[PDB]
Amino acid sequence: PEFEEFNGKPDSLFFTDGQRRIDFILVYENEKQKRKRQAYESNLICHGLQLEATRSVSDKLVFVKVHAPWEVLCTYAEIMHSFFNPATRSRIVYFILSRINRLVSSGIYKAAFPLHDCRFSERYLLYREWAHPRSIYKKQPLDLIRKYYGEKIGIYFAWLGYYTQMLLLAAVVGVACFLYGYLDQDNCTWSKEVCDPDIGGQILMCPQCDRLCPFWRLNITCESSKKLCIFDSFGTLIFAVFMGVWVTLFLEFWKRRQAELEYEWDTVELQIRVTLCASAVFFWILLIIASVIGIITSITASIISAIIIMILNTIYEKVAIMITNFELPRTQTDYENSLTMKMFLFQFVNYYSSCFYIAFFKGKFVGYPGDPVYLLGKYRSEECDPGGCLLELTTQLTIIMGGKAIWNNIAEVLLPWVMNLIGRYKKITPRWEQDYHLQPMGKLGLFYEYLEMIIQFGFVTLFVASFPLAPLLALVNNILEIRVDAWKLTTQFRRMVPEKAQDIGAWQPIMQGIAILAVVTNAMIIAFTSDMIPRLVYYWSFSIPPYGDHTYYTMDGYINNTLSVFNITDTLCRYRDFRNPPGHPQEYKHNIYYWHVIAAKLAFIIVMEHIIYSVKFFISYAIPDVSKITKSKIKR
Amino acid sequence: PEFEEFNGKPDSLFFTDGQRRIDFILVYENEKQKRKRQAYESNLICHGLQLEATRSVSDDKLVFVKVHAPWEVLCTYAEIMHSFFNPATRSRIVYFILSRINRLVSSGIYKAAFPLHDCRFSERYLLYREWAHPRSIYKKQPLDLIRKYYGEKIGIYFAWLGYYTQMLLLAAVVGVACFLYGYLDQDNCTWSKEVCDPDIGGQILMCPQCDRLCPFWRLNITCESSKKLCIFDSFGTLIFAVFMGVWVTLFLEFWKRRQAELEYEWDTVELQQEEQARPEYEAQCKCIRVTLCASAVFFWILLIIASVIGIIVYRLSVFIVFSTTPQMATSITASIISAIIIMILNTIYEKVAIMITNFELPRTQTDYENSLTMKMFLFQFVNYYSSCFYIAFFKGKFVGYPGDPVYLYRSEECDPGGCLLELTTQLTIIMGGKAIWNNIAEVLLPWVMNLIGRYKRKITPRWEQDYHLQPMGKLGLFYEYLEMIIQFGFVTLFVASFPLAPLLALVNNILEIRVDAWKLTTQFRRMVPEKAQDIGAWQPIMQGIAILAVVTNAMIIAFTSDMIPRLVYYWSFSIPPYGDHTYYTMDGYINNTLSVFNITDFKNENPYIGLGNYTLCRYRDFRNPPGHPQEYKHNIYYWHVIAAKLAFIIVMEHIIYSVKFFISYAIPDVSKITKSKIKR
Ligand SMILES: [Ca+2]
Ligand SMILES: [Ca+2]
Ligand SMILES: [Ca+2]
Ligand SMILES: [Ca+2]
Ligand SMILES: [Ca+2]
Ligand SMILES: [Ca+2]
């Protein structure tokens, strides 16, 4: 019932009078809608908040600024247990309005948001010094961003930076291991003997399809094998072990950082059907696993992958929102945890189903060219690429991390920017006005940034047994990522209602599960996917006299016998299996070597799982989750 | 001190005037110490406590000091720490006042201290009639009553032992079920019935185990053991091992549910004030000493390992004289000897560990408890499970073949059906001996000390009737917890051997809860109440045991239990390209697997020709038989088998770990009724 229009002040941090402060904005643009809106406004007035409705220069849309006086905000802060910064004021006013999401969900109320500082006073400082591209190198003023945006976004950015630093450590170690593998390429006997036309040229390997792809010569595989040997060497072993250790150190030191930030910022604040739903979600998960597996220069492929992942992500968001309400406990925290879990599961499938397929599905469920697996009209489950499943996984992971990360950040800046541009399309205006035209932060928007980084963490840790440059790629990605997120939140997206975050959130159990699954997955990649264990077993057994023709053990002769002599009966070929060349009473069957092979690597897998989990337990035991200095300031 | 003696009323917890009750007892019996003691007496006078000092009739030097607190003092100290004041509350308040006594008692000026009993064996009389008694062995425990009498930690220990007993009930029932399945299928054990078949079992010519004076013992001598061996490694045992993983999972979650229930019920969660330093720690006001202390532990760890190696040497030395089946008696005697040596070394390490932890400096008593827990649990783990891990995972594993056999010297071999029979014998011996002898000792030792104290030397008062009993000590139920954790390790870590492991163990627990209870009311004194919401460091330990158990169990089934070789035969070698049977069956297993050995031994001796006149003997290994281009050597079979076992380990580990994760995640650590009561 109050209206006053004034756009004369461009940098109006206050109302028309200037005494009050902007603590929120609600936009108002049938008769029963008007009655309900008036009832809510009267309730708001009775709570004590001071409201002011104004008409924009460009009419029909009316902005309703609000300002909770000092007494009411002080009382509500006491409920949670100029003096207060605008972040806390916005959070308090939003909590008051909550007892507003239901209103804005329907068409009765359009939108509401806290007001920013100014254009590009604190946003100017944290834009030029922190958010502007001119200041990429310098670290973020964590206290300043905590002051402005909030504790939840602050914890997100602090976690992002810490994860970047730990990525830098793992990345320098990965670069060391990568160069150790790369320099030792001329001494790689297998690569050279494959490259030899006398050996490599004569030997032949089996076709992937049924008379579609013909027989090919090892020359292409000889050329591709050098990169495989670069990514298939004991440097990969040492880096996988180091990554098993580094995940533990990462998690533990982040526990320490969480504790220290909890002390510094007082983040700790307080205020049958299930079985059927689980069965349905498992069915959907396997369905989309099948979808992605069936789905499966560099810039175009990366863009295509990004678009596919985007549309699939939209589908997952739709289906998860549809299915969550059936088991909704009418609890926002429980609902958001369930949505986090379901969206993460859909994304986990969408991203890592192809990777798991490359690792442990190509060449595994394919029988010998005599009677392979035939399921339906679709036939002959495709064999692994002759270059190497490790090579394919490294290619796919590099594509995903690098290209999809740069494209995701380009989208993260442009899409809000272009939406803001087309909104402004629809002269001087107050700096509190344009924040309406630019898009509001979506529901659980920061959940998406957290999910993106959790997906990157999964790519880096889960599949690090392939190539050690994944931490480096994710390091540069994080360096860009933190600043693009800062820029979009500073400029494109209006101010988000500050939250309180004791930790990052539901992604912590996700990260722990990813750590355990990453240990087991790295072990099974090294053994099952990479042929290093059969390489070593051939070396050590079939190179010493009892099984080999060499006086001292040497890997020579491995190539002449890794090809299982073949006669085509549904000249010689070999698929992904150590089989029995003719001369045995049974041929095309699990060979003497093959049991050596599986026993060796899965015994290596047992050893590695046990030692890595032992080291993780020892680290969690030895390394406290609370720092010494944190205890010293706690006892103060 | 108002020192005056009057035995008078034989059973009266009140003063000479009788107006006020009594909570505690301090016994004592020079000038500087006499000056110092009366100073603290004046300190308690300023603290308001009331103490009655009596010059006991039996010894004129002995003086008892009965301790009580006035109601105002009780109220203000109840304010300090978070018939109205129950005797347990009075005891806790009194000792908190005394602590705010450790140094004076340690210094020897005050001889001892304890909390009073009601009467002879009236809370104590009721607690001895319907509880703490062999006749009442089949009645539920008055847990709230023993909480009001003894204290919080005592209550939680007895609750934990009862809950362990309950869970072992179902564990033992399922174990008996699988054991019955194996016993029933014993009639159709093709390999064992083949062993006891003179046509095939009588033609088994197994190679000698030792070089000197050991014949080629045929399978006939072990036929009867084979009868009870097919039961030990049968698919029912495997199913029970999986169920044991499940029950291990179910155990601790419901325990912590019950523990939170008791936290709400007894209001265990109270003011955890800063702990007082131990008197010995403050007497002398460290990293090198700690590292030196750790070195002492690991040196003795090798010592018991060396004692275990002596058992290995003993079996090697004593089999020949037994031979002149002998190996069964040898194993039984060796297991008895190992149990005796474990019991002997247990007390030795108890004393030396108390001394060692005295040597190092814990800043608080709970730090002492944690360090002692770690050292004691480590040593007792090594003690009890060293022989068991040896039999399960070392004995017979690395013997090679008759040509160039392994030397150290000449490590032990094992029977065709594995050493799960010997491990079963060792486990049964250890656990049954633990029950019978350990519990008899648990009763007698405090009773024996009571008897010898009485012989030192009729109307006697409560304080005289109770001081002439062994004080419990500041540790207390540490050792019964350790005993039950050792039993848990035996039951779960080793359950792949015999499913009846809980059953007899169940027996123990029942008997256990009474014998201990007996000594806590009859033989020993009453122990001072302590506050302890949880059983403490033992709970993480069990978790580790749980995490260990799965692995161990899988390994025992894969490595120790020979079931995997038989499944490998039954699904891969009955085929005509590998055997002769048209379909899948287990017959021919023994004739097929254990390859022969023609007598061509390496000269690195050759006692085979000296000790017999046989041509080809059959060893229990899959290596190459004669006619092979590289004979007496590994073949396809052994690596097939080892891949089967390791893959079984991986499958069982991952499946069982997944199931444990699912159960812990699905079943919350807080009960719905518990949360409802908390909300109300
Ligand atoms: Ca990105
Ligand atoms: Ca982002
Ligand atoms: Ca820690
Ligand atoms: Ca006992
Ligand atoms: Ca006992
Ligand atoms: Ca649980």
Image: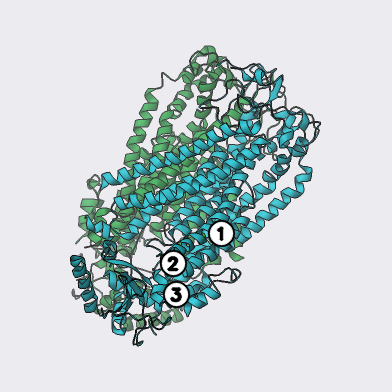
Chain colours: A green, B cyan
Q: Residue furthest top?
A: A198
Picture quarter containing residue B69? bottom left
Q: Is residue B244 above or below residue A548?
A: below
Mark 2 vs 3: CB contact within 8 A: no
Mark 3 vs 1: CB contact within 8 A: no
Bin the neighbour count of mark 2 within 10 Å (Cα to Cα): few under 14, some 14-19, many 20 and up.
few
x and y, in percent, of residue B235 in the image = 69, 46
Q: Is residue A633 left or right of residue A181?
A: left
Q: Which chain letter goes with mark 3? A: B
Measured Cα–Cα span from mark 3 to mark 1: 31 Å
x and y, in percent, of residue B309 in the image = 50, 36
Look at the numbered disc 2 and say if its residue's Cβ is closer than 8 Å to ligand 5.
Answer: no
- The amino acid at mark 1 is Leu
Name which of mark 3 and mark 1 comes first in the sequence.
3
| Foreground pick, B59 / A279 | B59
Disc 2, SS: helix
Measured Cα–Cα span from mark 2 to mark 1: 48 Å
Q: Which chain letter goes with mark 2? A: B
Bin the neighbour count of mark 1 within 10 Å (Cα to Cα): few under 14, some 14-19, many 20 and up.
some
Q: Is residue A33 left or right of residue B210?
A: left
Q: Which residue is mark 3?
A: B149
Do tags 2 and 3 sit on the same chain? yes
- The amino acid at mark 3 is Tyr
Picture quarter containing residue B211? top right
Q: Which residue is mark 2?
A: B454
- The amino acid at mark 2 is Arg
Q: Is residue A96 above or below residue B599?
A: below
